[PDB]
Image (cartoon, coloured by chain):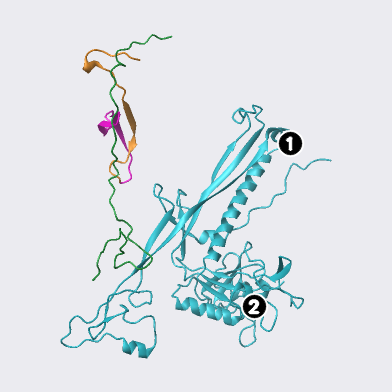
Amino acid sequence: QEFQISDPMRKRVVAYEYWGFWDIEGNGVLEPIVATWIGSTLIRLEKNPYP
Amino acid sequence: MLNYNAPTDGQKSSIDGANSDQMQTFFWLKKAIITARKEQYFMPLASVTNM
Amino acid sequence: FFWLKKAIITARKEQYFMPLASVTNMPKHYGKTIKVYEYVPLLDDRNINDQGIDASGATIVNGNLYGSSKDIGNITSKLPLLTENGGRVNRVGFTRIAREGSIHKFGFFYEFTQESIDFDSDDGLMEHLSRELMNGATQITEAVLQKDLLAAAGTVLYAGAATSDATITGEGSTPSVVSYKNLMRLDQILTENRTPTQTTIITGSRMIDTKVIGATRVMYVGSELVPELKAMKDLFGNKAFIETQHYADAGTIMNGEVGSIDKFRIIQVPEMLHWAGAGAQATGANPGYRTSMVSGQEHYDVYPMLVVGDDSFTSIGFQTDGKSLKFTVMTKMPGKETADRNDPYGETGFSSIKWYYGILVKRPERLALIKTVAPL
């Protein structure tokens, strides 16, 4: 519970990912996306990379 | 003249009759003001002993 | 004795007023109120403003040229005239009006026990209970809508010589029964208020004994008034009511239609609501009109007769998926889930239903109504 490594770069924090479909262009066609947020900050947002 | 007057502070616009007032009289940001968490100093100096 | 294993059930009651109502979408996170503007024309009397200058350059009380007045003298007096070296002479004003409506809540529920669930000889009881619950909910909602429409009418024409509900009586020199002239007057009023028509005239067919009918509006009556309408005679003393079989050819018969009189196509609604005891007191000289007992005195019964126009009203829809009304049903079967904290037996259960309903009346002049007594 209280574990913490000395170097700040090596601290572990919990994150979330969202694998799903969204209408990116609003014309009615669902396309895959991926999004990632930590706390209340959205860091990564792009299409599905895997073929 | 079709004056605007001031719908707030009790002075109806010229165009309005005796039943209706202005619908929108203020702009709302929709983003709130929030306060951050207070820091914790004595908590890191504690190692847990699971019971 | 041997149980038949089949039940006797009565179906729903068909609903007429609910299908008419149009639905206005209201998003949540706003409140319990909806509002619209209404821009009055230039020349109507409702255009009460303070921006008037007459042709002589002096200020005047009214800003609309001339009101809804057809008098030739008045029009000639208040015409806008301009001299050649004209400037700052005639001014006009404008006005808008707002209307609103609100949403109200409803609901009811019932309870049952687990021993009743199991030991009961009949199987499938809870299906029956669900069926009656849903039917009751639908019937109640339709009744509420009809009640609000009857209360919110804009054009009211009492029959006979009455003035208010207390005056509508069926005894004396002039009983308050619907007449041909009353229907003609109702048509005249609706035509003046610019209410759009609903149907179209029905020309003839080539088949023997087929009359020609030119009604153009739809009128809802109760079940009690149908004999009175059938007995009506027009101005020249002939029959007025024309039954449906005469003009079924070369036309389309609407649902629940009994006939056509003058310029209205009558429609019978089984669940039509009537006031009770609204009329004046009834003595022993009753010619045979329906009465009712209020506070020990027999009062006459005042009856509807309603002509809903187009775009008159809309039904606010709160999370109804673009429908007039949507229900929410919950059930908890007995067991550990219903094992009460003070009673872990868990022998009971329940089922509940609820909804949100509200109505916005955009234009109340189009709604029309006639109040009459109904023969026994």
Which residue, given by chain and number where applicable, does mark 1 sit on? Answer: C120
Q: Return the x and y of residue C331 as percentages of the image width and height.
A: 59, 38
* Magenta stretch holds residue A39: yes
* Residue C177, numbered circle: 2
A28 or C324: nearer the eye?
C324
Residues C47 and C306: in front is C47
Give the image quarter of residue C141: bottom right
Outermost right residue: C1
Q: Pinpoint the chain carrying mark 1.
A: C
- Residue under the point 46% across and 53% down: C317
Residue C120, horizontal then vertical, whole percent: 74, 36
Q: What's the amino acid at mark 1?
A: Asp
Residue in the picture at 22% in, 86% down: C82
In the picture shown, does residue C217 fall above or below B8? Answer: below
- Mark 2: which secondary structure? loop
Horizontally, is C29 left or right of C90 in the view? right
Q: Which SS class for mark 1?
A: loop
Look at chain C in the picture and name its colour: cyan
Quadrant that contains the N terminus of chain C: top right
Badge 2 density bin: few <14, some 14–19, many ≥20, Cα 10 Å:
many
User: Which chain is tinted orange?
Assistant: A
Query: Which mark is on residue C106?
Result: none
Q: Position of residue C24 (x, y in %)?
A: 43, 56
- Chain where mark 2 sits: C
Colour in which chain B is drawn: green
